[PDB]
């Protein structure tokens, strides 16, 4: 007769579980670039800083794309509950791999492991949350809200803890901290799920029928075949540097959506571009803005990675406010494409803001941290409008995020100290201009 804030106790298991995975994940991201910069300056890794930035970006991209595969493997083959478990193990392993004395050798293994891991875990945890409520129940809206608040809790404290740890005991002890985080998540999951989750999800809910096996295999086989063929063809011509490999992945990512657009509502062709653009800016925060914090701000008294805490902090502060807004502005609303429009403008503003300090002071010194503070605040305000309503204006919503990041892999190469004021301005203005185009067509789309 004890609930977790009104909700079934099972929610608390899924809360704790997803909260530590988000911890391991955003904790790692918050120092991964800097770590990669560290490797470079010691001779162990032979890439440029720009390429490192593009590895941070494409890494994100493949995590998002993998998520769309993950629901399938769960539902037709191994079952949802074990999927989350072994996703969790694969993730724990990537982190362990980094916290060991090796160098660049490990880095690539680790990246593969977390990509496949997060692929299994991330979509299926959301699913299992749906499982807690009868499809008649209306606590479900409260439930998902709570669960999401746990996602952002973990994201928020992770840079604080891991960033500190890195400063004190170095990079390897900091990465192990993320392994342990995922481990705690696993412990709560295993034992708490035997107590609080349905055993009906120990199995795929839609097993392959006998005649379906051979087809599936033929497809997977052709897929890998051609992919291997492309890699082979690439290494003959002499296209074997890392940026060439990133370029291949950038391609694969873009193709998949394009390829699936192949006329009742072609409405979202411009809405999708809008989403895709927004995520690119938001995702640059952990790369470009991360880079700006290490180089253009005075962060001698604190761990620079602590800035990464600002993104999930504003989502939490903004959340109770906007919950109220859609009730207290109930009768006469911004339509869903007014929302995309305004959102994208605000993301555009967060970058223009960043053009100012260089325009005014030049690019040769340091500036107040608060610039970043203001930037982050503007973009999250943009996310508030886009992330909730956009969902049902579901494969594709994991996909807009992946396309956005794939694009970063190419654009963040252009950022640097001399290009600063231009980069922020072209992107910035570029985005506002597409947003105003979207308030106009906001009318014609509805259908
Ligand atoms: C659709 C996107 C690709 C997702 C990757 C799928 C995994 C790759 C190959 C799976 C083929 C193995 C078949 C497993 C299986 O359950 O055998 C059928 C068995 O249940 C007899 O009914
Ligand atoms: C770098 C490549 C590593 C990939 C290794 C692949 C491992 C993926 C998942 C781990 C085992 C999941 C299946 C375990 C299970 O309980 O189901 C077994 C059986 O039902 C499958 O038909
Ligand atoms: C329950 C899961 C356990 C998670 C794994 C625990 C972490 C294991 C080893 C990480 C500690 C550092 C190992 C040695 C090391 O190179 O530390 C860095 C130090 O040598 C300075 O470079
Ligand atoms: C599964 C869908 C595949 C569609 C493939 C379409 C295009 C395929 C190959 C063309 C580009 C391959 C990689 C690009 C590249 O290496 O350029 C970088 C190089 O110029 C720098 O050395
Ligand atoms: C509360 C919202 C505030 C939003 C701020 C509005 C945007 C302000 C400035 C954006 C453009 C500044 C860059 C001006 C510029 O083009 O400088 C280039 C050159 O002339 C000097 O480097
Ligand atoms: C609800 C609105 C309250 C807060 C709004 C934030 C302020 C609005 C626009 C700020 C644009 C940049 C300001 C430029 C500036 O102050 O430069 C001078 C700076 O060096 C301080 O000396
Ligand atoms: C909300 C109001 C936004 C403020 C308006 C945008 C202008 C922001 C900064 C302007 C600084 C000077 C404008 C560009 C500039 O650098 O011109 C000076 C040039 O001769 C030497 O760089
Ligand atoms: C939410 C908190 C955001 C952080 C607030 C940023 C403003 C606080 C401090 C600004 C920089 C000065 C730090 C103290 C310091 O050591 O100044 C350096 C000294 O050499 C003065 O020249
Ligand atoms: C069917 C739609 C076709 C439109 C393709 C969408 C855009 C594709 C790729 C982005 C181009 C970025 C151009 C800048 C760039 O990456 O070059 C700089 C750097 O990569 C040097 O290698
Ligand atoms: C068709 C829709 C496209 C709308 C805009 C798409 C992306 C928005 C702005 C692109 C940012 C430009 C990045 C390159 C750049 O800033 O070059 C100037 C500077 O870097 C000198 O090299």
Image (tube, rainbow, N blue to C red):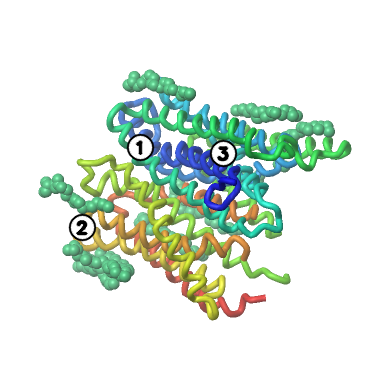
Q: Nearer the viewer, mark 2 or mark 1?
A: 1
Q: Label 2 crowding class (10 Å Cα cut-off): few <14, some 14-19, many 20+?
A: few
Instruction: Residue under label 1, please give it.
Output: 161
Label 1 element class: helix
Disc 2 Cβ-to-ligand 7 distance below 8 Å: yes
Q: Quadrant of the C terminus?
A: bottom right
Position of residue 353 relative to residue 63, above or below, is below
Real-space Cα distance between discs 2 and 1?
A: 34 Å
- Label at residue 429: none
Residue 153 in view here: yes
Position of residue 94 relative to residue 382, above or below, is above
- Label at residue 118: 3
Instruction: Residue under label 2, please give it.
Output: 362
> Which residue is at the front of the view, 70 or 228?
70
Question: Which is nearer the N-term, disc 2 or disc 1?
Answer: 1
Q: Quadrant of residue 89?
A: top right
> Which residue is at the front of the view, 425 or 238?
425
Identified at 58% across, 79% down, the residue is 443
């Amino acid at each position: 007769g004890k609930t977790f804030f009104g909700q079934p106790l099972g929610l608390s298991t899924l809360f704790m579980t997803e909260m530590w995975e988000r911890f391991s994940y955003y904790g790692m991201r918050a120092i991964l670039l800097y770590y990669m910069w560290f490797l470079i300056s010691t001779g162990d890794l032979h890439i440029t800083r720009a390429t490192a930035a593009s590895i941070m970006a494409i890494y994100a991209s493949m995590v998002y794309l993998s998520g769309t595969i993950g629901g399938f493997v769960a539902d037709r083959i191994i079952g949802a509950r074990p999927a989350v478990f072994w996703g969790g193990v694969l993730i724990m392993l990537g982190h362990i791999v980094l916290a060991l004395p090796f160098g660049a050798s490990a880095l690539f293994g680790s990246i593969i492991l977390i990509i496949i891991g997060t692929g299994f875990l991330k979509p299926n945890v959301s699913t299992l949350v749906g499982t807690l409520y009868d499809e008649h129940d209306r606590r479900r809206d409260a439930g998902f809200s709570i669960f999401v608040f746990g996602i952002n809790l973990g994201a928020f404290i992770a840079p604080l803890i891991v960033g500190a740890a890195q400063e004190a005991a170095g990079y390897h002890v900091a990465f192990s901290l993320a392994a342990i985080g995922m481990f705690i998540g696993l412990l709560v999951y295993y034992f708490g799920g035997k107590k609080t989750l349905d055993p009906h999800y120990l199995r795929p809910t839609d097993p392959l029928a006998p005649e379906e096996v051979k087809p599936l295999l033929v497809k997977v086989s052709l897929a890998v075949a051609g992919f291997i063929a492309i890699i082979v063809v690439m290494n003959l011509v002499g296209w074997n540097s890392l940026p060439a490999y990133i370029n291949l992945l950038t391609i694969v990512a873009i193709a998949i959506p394009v390829f699936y657009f192949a006329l009742r509502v072609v409405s979202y062709i411009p809405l999708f571009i809008a989403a895709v653009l927004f995520w690119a800016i938001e995702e640059q925060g952990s790369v470009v803005l991360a880079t700006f914090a290490a180089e253009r701000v005075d962060s001698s008294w604190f761990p620079v990675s602590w800035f990464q805490s600002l993104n999930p902090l504003f989502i939490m502060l903004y959340t109770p406010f906007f919950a109220w807004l859609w009730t207290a502005w109930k009768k006469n609303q911004p339509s869903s494409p007014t929302k995309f429009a305004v959102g994208l403008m605000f993301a555009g503003l967060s970058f223009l803001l960043m053009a100012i300090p260089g325009a005014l002071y030049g690019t040769s010194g340091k500036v107040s941290p608060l610039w970043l503070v203001g930037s982050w605040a503007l973009v999250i305000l943009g996310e508030m409008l886009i992330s909730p309503v956009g969902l049902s204006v579901m494969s594709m919503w994991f996909l807009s995020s992946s396309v956005g990041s794939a694009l970063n892999a190419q654009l963040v190469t252009l950022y640097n100290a001399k290009s600063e004021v231009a980069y922020f301005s072209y992107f910035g203005l570029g985005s506002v201009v597409l947003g105003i185009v979207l308030v106009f067509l906001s009318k014609r789309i509805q259908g």
